[PDB]
Image (cartoon, rainbow, N blue to C red; front, side, top):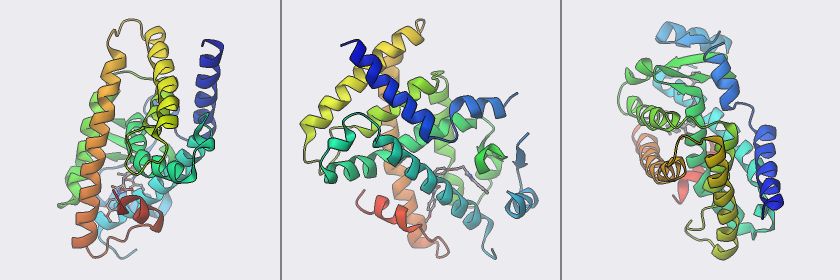
Length: 255
Ligand SMILES: COc1ccc(N2C(=O)[C@@H](Cc3cccc(OCCc4nc(-c5ccccc5)oc4C)c3)[C@H]2C(=O)O)cc1
């Protein structure tokens, strides 16, 4: 009710600090304050050697899967630390994760993105937005909409404490399909959402409607992920050399 709100937020923020190697503050330091730039095929090959016979498109997106698999592993550890998450039924734990991970992945991805490109290889590399756009279809259509989301998400000027509470709220959506105990999850989300609002009002006193603007972003992420999943399916089925990591196969499966 105030001490309990500090306690909920503390545990979430700390689980974020603990579990995510890359975060907004670290990313903004590196994108400022120097990362190897990938802006063409020569620089790509240079980075691959330092940071297969397959197409350039195939290699880039093979490496992405390694990054996303690490993030899904990190988000899982973060979820287990959200107060209440671990007392959930087991079917609900994996359901919340299956549906929540990519929404949370793309919200957090924004921290490493600017209008010109994004960090790769733990912030040791920077891959250009224009190089990504120069890939042949459908590979050039993968990242562009995430840059588009990210430019608008980054304009909200969130920091890591905001983001941590946001991500916990994404993970605890009571409206995931197949959920068995929606009432307990919904009680979890309400506290997170309530402390997020209060945190946003004190942290950002000049952005009146930051709370609702950020909630609109959940709907945008949900849309961004449904579209990404469709595109992953399409590439998987049309583009032979596009294997999918076995952890990702099951996430995408019943989406
Ligand atoms: C079967 O077909 C496909 C097609 C596409 C994908 N995926 C995505 O797209 C990934 C989405 C994703 C998730 C997390 C980080 C990402 O971006 C991290 C930046 C980044 N790092 C590199 C990179 C370059 C050179 C060398 C090292 C890293 O490139 C990029 C764009 C991207 C992955 C996914 O859906 O999990 C999966 C299967």
